Length: 165
Length: 165
Image (cartoon, rainbow over all chains, first blue to last red; front, side):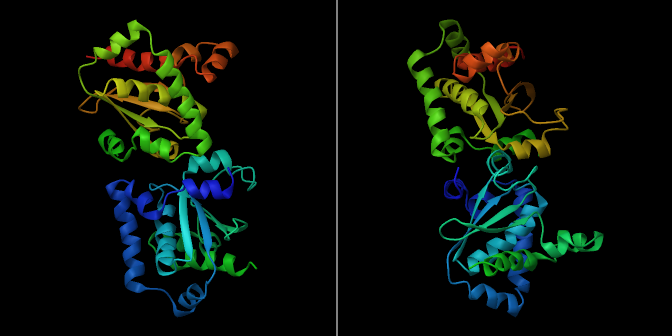
């Protein structure tokens, strides 16, 4: 299926979360509250506000995955603040079946977030975790699992949008 | 999660089908029409009508899978004819994450259909294909992919219900 066809059958975040176990919806609620209370740095907030074109994020994720709970709570926050961004979420299994060849991936690590423009051209991708976490060791991964890198998922995605033209 | 918790977040067949690509919904429509036109043997139809207790089928499946398209179209038919049976469908990924240990499976072949009673006790399972297809060769698998074993998915499931007490 084309990226447009996949984004069409993808679910929105509210629906995605609504299909999760009570425990998993509570994990997402926890990461959401951290952003709602702490907010975001002003430099990042400014970069978000300056996004004036429409971007589509095609995600492969699942509500039982801790990395999806973490990073998608973040990207939902961003999208609710900046509705020029929109997420649609398909399954890991569907990504394994239809996205592995074109993306040149042997396996699908979730969340896989594909950043597309309005004509569904692929601008880049975020895979599993923020790059500052993927460059780190035990310490960074641990703070991340605690929700201390939520702003990095947003920053990474903005970076891909910014990196394009 | 318990089998009750998993069946609760499972989607019904109509919803499951509604999230599929137009092409995949057409495949399901095709297998449905074959049952709607041809029907079922009278011996099988009788065994279906005699199911007087409530049974819950917890399925792991995905709309892009040909085996799920085939066998779940069949089991939906059965359930619409015999509403003492009810399907709820969760993802392959969630089955990989939460059902592999308790079922003693190294991998999840879909559809995985777990047959449970009303107190969510596991009576048995159907895995990927009907047993008469799994015992066959190229010829049987080919007729199966063409939809010539739809009645066997139903029969297998009734057999598990019948095999219990």
